[PDB]
Image 1 (cartoon, rainbow, N blue to C red):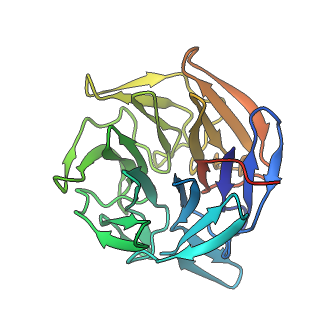
Image 2 (image 1 turned 135 degrees about the vertical axis):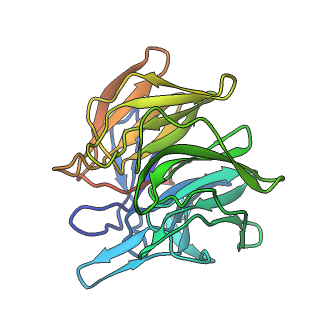
Image 3 (image 1 turned 120 degrees about the vertical axis):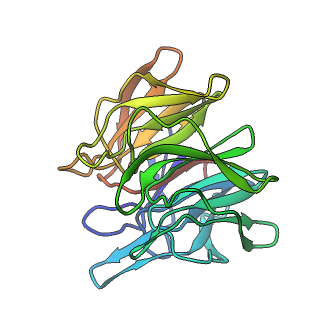
Length: 288
């Protein structure tokens, strides 16, 4: 199952919905404890983690440092220890069962900080900061290395990408993308880092480009059918899924799937309601 948590459409949502690519169905599950947009989702030990984001309530607007975990066996949410700072429009990646929270904003502060979460101790430790302040950053893990791609620094939208070495504890710059992208969807498929969509300060983008480590190069692939930024992205059974996003006029509910063997995109499903800024991950389906 593909899970989408949170999101945004006129305000921040607490929806938690799971998609079945063979059923067609969307499952409504336990709402997030607090409505949140601009968050990230990941899966460690089967549990679905929802990280950071912001609560845009009609009453107030607060960036979040919260970490919350969802259990598909219990269909229940449980809070974890929070990060050191609120991180809206965050990126996250998993390395050896540890959650890396990357960038994001807190009010006017644009983070370059990065922190690591250890699920076995429910603890958060700060690691080496990034070379760039990046909110709306895409994050991926390839061969146990953490990559931070694109983003916005508060003044400029970025096309650069950097790599973090966990044991070396430092970041080093890599080849920049062909396109400046903030709020793109970044994932790993096979051994290539995919950057899809995003916003370049002027247009929402449908272009997709993938980074090959062996040649240290970003090459363009088949573009999506719909430009979108602040989209959700995940990989399921060797195919990429992008969910939602914002195209400058509407909050999309389109869900596109990319088949790498044919370099093509297809529209498989719509979400129950358009939204952007979701967390998205894949884990076992819940329990009847």
